[PDB]
Image: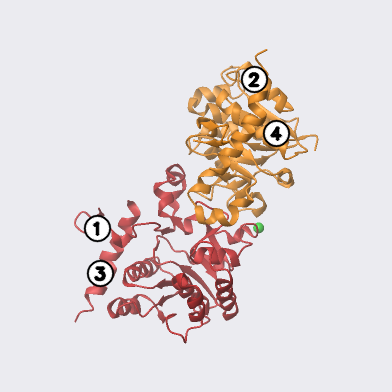
Chain colours: A orange, B red
Amino acid sequence: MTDQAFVTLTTNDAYAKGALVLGSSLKQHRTSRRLAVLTTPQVSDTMRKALEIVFDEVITVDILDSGDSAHLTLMKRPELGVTLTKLHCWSLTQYSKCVFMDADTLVLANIDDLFEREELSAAPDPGWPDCFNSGVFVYQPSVETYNQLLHVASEQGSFSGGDQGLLNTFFNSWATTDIRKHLPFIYNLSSISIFSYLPAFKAFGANAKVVHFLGQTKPWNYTYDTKTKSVRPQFLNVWWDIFTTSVVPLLQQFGL
Amino acid sequence: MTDQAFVTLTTNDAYAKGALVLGSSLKQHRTSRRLAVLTTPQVSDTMRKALEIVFDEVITVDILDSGDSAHLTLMKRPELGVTLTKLHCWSLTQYSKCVFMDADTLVLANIDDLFEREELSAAPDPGWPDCFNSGVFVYQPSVETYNQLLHVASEQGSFSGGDQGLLNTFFNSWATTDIRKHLPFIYNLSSISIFSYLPAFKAFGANAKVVHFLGQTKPWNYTYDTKTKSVRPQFLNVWWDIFTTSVVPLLQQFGL
Ligand SMILES: [Cl-]
């Protein structure tokens, strides 16, 4: 649909790499949706221009600017920079529904069916499964929800010191209400649960639709051998394949 | 209710300690339900007699006996000893509904409301949260279900090499169907998620109703200082308090 989007976020050039890989993965699996990326001014012109090619829309967010609605809350809780920036995904009222995906996710199959879901649909978090992981979620842009999230951020902050605590606190019926708001874990498959919980992977992890690179060493903190097509494991190598294949050439293209 | 029960299982004297602590924890939080314990002949007379005091019913299961319905399946899949024994929880047709709890769980509050639940209700597993953890679950005893589980055990075994894989495979709609069959994580709170996922604990882990001692070192593999009332952490110490207070005296009582 025209007014639906995957939305991601990048606050720096490291994460812009992820966002570019994510965007590409989404294009590769023939999404019929828009691709939007929240970006900060800290993202350089080269990453930016590549984001402009990969994404239908590049939105600038500067919570460091006092014009930003999140800025006073950033002052109150300065650890919440990334969180308050991320929450701007709710400002995107040019879209009726979006799938937010962190820039450290990777799409391995079309996940457009996520748009059948209602706010707030998200996959369970490993570790504390009565929380949803905020790495992938379905939400409806709204200035009201935005303001309410912003307000909760101000009042409580996040029990996680990040967006996950904040989102779970506001969307707190997730655990106990409407199983359709549980996204299958395969739509936000923790790369940790692929290596750590290895019995459950073998049986279901070949079904993965989205890899969420958690931790730790993010995909781009790895060394990739372009000859062997392998890092210094399966999923890191898909990410790097996309990076090497689609993203680097788009990045090297901006220097002329 | 008269014909409802918590059911646990012990295949040896190490686990009988857990079962005795579990049973006691259940009595301590004034359950109105029956307490049943599947036991193997490998459980010694002393553990047994103490089980007889703590539990309303002590049921003997010997899958090593060829009279047992599970025995031929044990022959086919000998790694499934514990699993096939556990599955006998479904034979307990003297009960209309039961809560099965592994002998490495600990009850910290009345959880009798679990009997409002239908088969198969269970808490999500940490690590792979689209599986339920088989440490605590609500089920309806039935020879049909039993036979069907036994049959699946024979055909597929368990993708986990344990009961969890088997149960998830048979009760495979759990992830996607009926949010009421998701037991809050606090009814099967992984002791690992208490130490490992520490941000989510502080906010919700004080609400714990059942601790599931996973791993690893089981509670009884720890040294307990009875003077300091502490092990060699909060939950280990509740377990040991119950053990020292209620269980050991019941065990020392059998030697005369
Ligand atoms: Cl439901």
From the top left corner, tell me how far across and down residue B107 is, in percent: 41, 62
Whole-number angstrom distance, CA of label 3 to CA of label 4: 60 Å
**What residue is shown with label 1?**
B223
Q: Amino acid at mark 1?
A: Thr
Q: Label 4: few (<14), some or many (≥20) within 10 Å?
A: some
Residue closer to the observer: B113 or B148: B148
Residue closer to the observer: A71 or A133: A133
Location of the C terminus of chain B by quadrant is bottom left
* Residue at image point 59% right, 51% down: A205
* Residue at image point 49% right, 25% down: A78
**What residue is shown with label 2?**
A252
Q: Amino acid at mark 4?
A: Ser
State the SS at label 2: helix
Q: Is residue A23 visible?
A: yes
* Residue A142: numbered disc: 4
**What residue is shown with label 3?**
B248
**Which chain is disc 3 placed on?**
B
Whole-number angstrom distance, CA of label 2 to CA of label 4: 37 Å
Please say if B209 is above or below B70: above
State the SS at label 4: loop
**Which chain is disc 4 placed on?**
A
**Which chain is disc 2 placed on?**
A
